[PDB]
Image 1 (cartoon, rainbow, N blue to C red):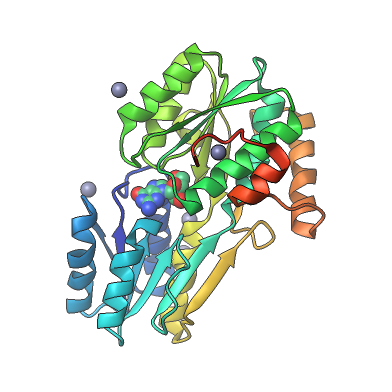
Image 2: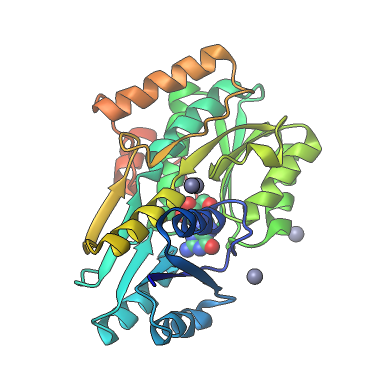
Length: 311
Ligand SMILES: Nc1nc2c(ncn2[C@@H]2O[C@H](CO)[C@@H](O)[C@H]2O)c(=O)[nH]1
Ligand SMILES: [Zn+2]
Ligand SMILES: [Zn+2]
Ligand SMILES: [Zn+2]
Ligand SMILES: [Zn+2]
Ligand SMILES: [Zn+2]
């Protein structure tokens, strides 16, 4: 039997977003492909190495490390276990024959939801709650702020780094404070912490924007959209490659054109004018007409010092 193991990050498989979507894709892979799937949650980074080792020792054909913080542990395990195949989501630093890097152009989807936030705010203040700061996480920020400003040059983006992907209290408190200070749309790129962000928006009667999966069921009257990142499909696809015997190492990048990132399929709360505007911007990115900044220098060159979490 083909066995695929998932090592999840601190967020947990019930995060409503990143890890939950990765796991959902593996559950689908089990149903459709016949692979046997199991996950191991890591309470802290001390659990990364033994969780990887447990799948190695049990004969798993592929170990999927979900999240950029697993990179160091994945590299070390891949070097020490040349016959073991690994995949890692959201980090592309590892160049080894047994490692596939699954990357997502999240700045593209974040830009689109920033257009939504800029067009929907009535106070000209919107919020961004990020789970941690890192190169990949800042791509959410750069895209979102660029979208907000392109849609609404006079909008202010309030920003907060929760320093956790698994703290719903931090998410709720930060959202509530932003709302007290006038924000009326809040986007999170914060994993499980975002469950708190969404609850804070719902409680205050404001708009939220979710991430990774279509988070609208968590607050159907308050979610405008979500910046989708199809970690489910990427995990399914690599499971398929394992089953077929054609896993390739290196970088696989999922973008808007590949449908690997997107805005959510639920659009019930988007005015037709807004949906049309965002959909045109999506096709312009897909067709190459416009490019979203995803690094500090590119973002600052166009928007100045307005992203405060990268300094
Ligand atoms: N390293 C890591 N990143 C996460 C986690 N949860 C969310 N993220 C990131 O935050 C984004 C928004 O949830 C995801 O697409 C990931 O990039 C987690 O538990 N660990
Ligand atoms: Zn658990
Ligand atoms: Zn089926
Ligand atoms: Zn607090
Ligand atoms: Zn799915
Ligand atoms: Zn900055």
